[PDB]
């Protein structure tokens, strides 16, 4: 069945004329090959959708395990192209065990070599879980992962999927270096991208792209899952960086169960492969599930604290508009040993908005006030409260912000901090 | 003397007369002390519910951090007694910062010294997240947040009692004792129902395996009830137990049972606690909402947990182990230390009837509608005779040994003892 022929799929993915088979073709249901991706030595394996639906058996699984063993030994990235209905039922338990051995190999590779899955067709049973164990999953629209968060990148078509896969091994395996000249040349007034009013929502994504190199794609992960949080890989003066940013357009930009988990997973992934982090903070609080279930955000929030806390790659924080309460601590604060914390001049760092704060601290005085005088008293109390608290100057005194910067130098200030940090220690 | 008094609470927790304060008592909202729990040196801190509802401030947080540093230095377990509304609003960002420094100390301690949280009063904001970063959380009733609490006590005093026991489980792990294993052997199989199609609570099985004297400290009994996990002692040695529970969801794996098992596996692995995995699982379930996202993601995490695990971990198949769930429940392919099976156990891709319906679907379809439902039975009968049995699994090599259920304890104990403390 030509289009799903594994040699062809492997050929479309690798650099032209670089494919070198790791074993002889057969009817096992997988073909594994060595090759190159823009010069980078890469291992890949393709399930054979032209043989029994691509169903996995002992012999095919063995080829994948050998492929993994090969990539591990040479420290090469390994890409799996997936199209498969699951384990070969007629092989019984023997196939279950072999599928398990595939899992076990992916686990040995975890955080040691990059693992990229490209799902180009139906993926079920063991063929759904395999990709779930890898670092990044690319899905072509002629696919579905069955047996939401599982899929990181959705491509336009099978060829686009290979193209994104190729870029991903570039981001992991040709990380480059920071360049000050390039960082400065790309500087613009990122602050101008915000709305005029502090109360208005906006998509954070243009801020992100303005920080990142103009001529390089921002590869956003899981865009439609936990949309209050944006995460992804891009280049900053040519250097691969990971970006996390609250997106005020969705849920006020609040943290919650899924956004915390999304951010936590992405942090551990960048940490594992030496990829520095830009954390763009504009977060006013956090949220329970619709049913007032707080257990999710607690558990996942703790996982996020733990991820930043244990992180050792450079990770710099930029407060754009506001950062409040517990969500402030979680978003790469000084208390979790952020490399450096930056703030735009009109940013707020506080427990909560002044009016909210004052409305708690002086609940009794406010309620004792005459109804028609109450709001004026509330406003006046709030004005004094923010005279003394919430501002960048105050945050600099405390030492939770390191530097107030000109928004027009954002891109070059972040770059300077990341470049001059140690590769490891936080 | 007020019940919420931090010195009182610390004194009730520690061995009588052992308390030694780590700082001068003050208005900070925290008191921290050294002491012993059945002989072992332990550090503890207690939030002061009498001062501002126990709200966390800069100076109180500093006492907590110091206690963590002290514990990290001496490699002592550290117990937090929590009763607190969260950060002191009026101290502003400084209090937030200090709370974050408490988080950071807990993270530095993570997997290095045991951390126990005893929540005896209202706990909110930063005071809910503190405990969430520890290893085991005990809650007194007097204090929706599903999955966060590991153990519910009967009251405050019982909570200290369970906490004290947890220190012993983590810091007095002991040695396996082959003679005590044997002395406790019984026919555990006799606890199974007559029919293999009948559901049962797996907890008495777990109980019969564990030491008859020692309590079974179940974690999160009410969350993900198709999965049972907890700590106990096997022949005097602290072990972790995971067991499918056929009583709920047919004992199937699903999104939250995979999560519950994975977190527990990672905890035991962190502290050198060997695992006993009691398997009776017919398959796995999707979400709500036939979405597979949760089970795919959490299941993957469970695979990762067993795969990377280096403590001894032995599997015992009692009745069923099917398909993908078979793989995940500590199979040979994920380097299980050893895999045991009772004589009647099935290790298979699915039920024989179901298996045949797919393996022979074209041939079943091509048969006359009247003589099909009888051919199905015939083919299932042949299938059942050549696949699915322990003997088959033994030959394949995914079961190491079929065992007399009357010798479960000693067999498990022998396999756990012979394994290295770290490999697999
Ligand atoms: C009474 N008010 C307080 O105590 C303030 C406060 C302080 C810390 C805190 O901890 C965390 N919050 C999050 C929120 C999201 C997330 F993903 C992680 C965390 S950790 C939570 C808090 O309400
Ligand atoms: C076509 N049929 C198959 O391919 C059978 C099959 C094989 C492997 C598999 O992988 C996993 N399953 C789970 C289930 C729960 C869980 F918590 C983890 C895993 S991993 C899943 C499978 O349906």
Image (cartoon, coloured by chain):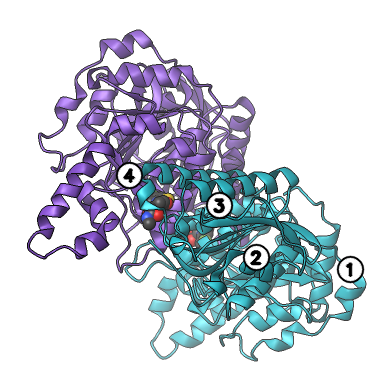
Chain colours: A cyan, B purple
Q: Which residue is mark 4?
A: B220
Which residue is at the front of the view, B366 or B376?
B366
| Dot 3 and dot 1 within a common chain | no
The chain carrying label 1 is A
- In the rendered image, the quadrant that contains the C terminus of chain B is top right
Chain of the residue where label 2 is placed in the rendered structure: A
- Which residue does the image show at 23% across and 47% down from the upper left? B352
State whether residue B232 appears in this view: yes
Q: Nearer the viewer, residue A194 or B407?
A: B407
Q: Residues within 10 Å of mark 1 (few under 14, many from 20)?
A: some
Q: In this figure, which residue is indicated by the disc labeled 1?
A: A179
| Image position, residue B418 (x, y; %) | 47, 17
Q: Residue at x 45, y 88 (%)?
A: A373
Label 3 belongs to which residue? B57
Q: Which residue is mark 2?
A: A10
Front of the two marks 1 and 4: 1
Which type of secondary structure does the marked residue at label 4 adopt? loop
Q: Chain of mark 4?
A: B
Provide residue A129's location: percent of width, then percent of height: 46, 56
Is A419 in front, or is A298?
Answer: A419
Q: Looking at this view, is A267 or A336 the one in front?
A: A267
| Residue A78 visible in this rendered orientation of the protein | no
Q: Are marks 4 and 2 in contact (CB under 8 Å)?
A: no
Q: Going from the N terminus, do you reach mark 3 or mark 4 first? A: 3
Residue with the most extreme left position:
B370
Q: Mark 4, mark 2: which one is toward the viewer?
A: 2
Which residue is painted at 16% across and 54% down in the image? B376
Res A271 quadrant in image? bottom right
């Amino acid at each position: 069945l030509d289009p799903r022929d594994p040699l062809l799929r492997l050929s479309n993915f690798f650099d032209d004329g670089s494919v070198e088979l790791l074993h002889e073709r057969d009817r096992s249901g997988v073909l594994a090959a060595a090759g190159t991706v823009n010069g980078v030595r890469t291992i890949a394996f393709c399930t054979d959708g032209t043989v029994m639906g691509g169903a996995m058996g002992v012999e095919g699984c063995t080829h994948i395990v050998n492929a993994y063993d090969t990539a591990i030994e040479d420290q090469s990235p390994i890409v799996g192209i997936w199209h498969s209905g699951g384990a070969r039922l007629a092989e019984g338990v023997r196939a279950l065990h072999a599928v398990g051995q595939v899992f076990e190999a992916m686990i040995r590779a975890s955080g040691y070599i990059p693992q990229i899955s490209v799902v180009v067709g139906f993926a079920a049973g063991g063929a759904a879980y395999g990709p779930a164990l890898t670092d990044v999953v690319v899905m072509a629209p002629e696919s579905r992962v069955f047996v939401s968060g599982v899929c990181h990148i959705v491509a336009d078509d099978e060829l686009d999927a290979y193209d994104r896969g190729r870029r991903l091994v570039g981001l992991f395996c040709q990380q480059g270096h920071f360049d000050r000249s390039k960082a400065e040349a790309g500087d613009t007034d990122i602050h101008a991208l915000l709305p005029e009013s502090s109360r208005r929502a906006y998509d954070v994504r243009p801020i992100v792209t303005a920080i990142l190199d103009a001529d390089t794609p921002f590869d956003e992960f899981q865009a439609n899952w936990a949309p209050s949080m944006v995460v992804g890989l891009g280049r900053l003066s040519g250097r691969t960086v990971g970006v996390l940013a609250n997106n005020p357009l969705r849920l006020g930009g609040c943290l919650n169960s899924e956004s915390a988990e999304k951010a936590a997973r992405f942090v551990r992934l960048c940490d594992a492969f030496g990829i520095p982090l830009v954390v763009v903070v504009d977060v006013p609080g956090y949220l329970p599930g619709v049913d007032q279930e707080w257990g999710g955000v607690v558990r996942r929030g703790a996982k996020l604290l733990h991820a930043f806390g244990e992180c050792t790659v450079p990770r710099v924080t930029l407060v754009t508009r506001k950062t409040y309460g517990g969500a402030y601590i979680a978003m790469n604060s000084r208390s979790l040993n952020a490399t450096k914390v930056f703030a735009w001049p009109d940013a707020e760092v506080a427990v909560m908005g002044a009016k909210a704060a004052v409305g708690i601290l002086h609940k009794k005085k406010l309620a004792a006030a005459p109804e028609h005088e109450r709001e004026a008293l509330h406003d006046q109390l709030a004005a004094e409260h923010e005279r003394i608290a919430g501002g960048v100057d105050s945050a600099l005194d405390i030492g939770v912000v390191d530097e107030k910067i000109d928004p027009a130098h954002t891109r070059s200030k972040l770059t300077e901090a990341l470049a001059q940090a140690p590769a490891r220690r936080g």
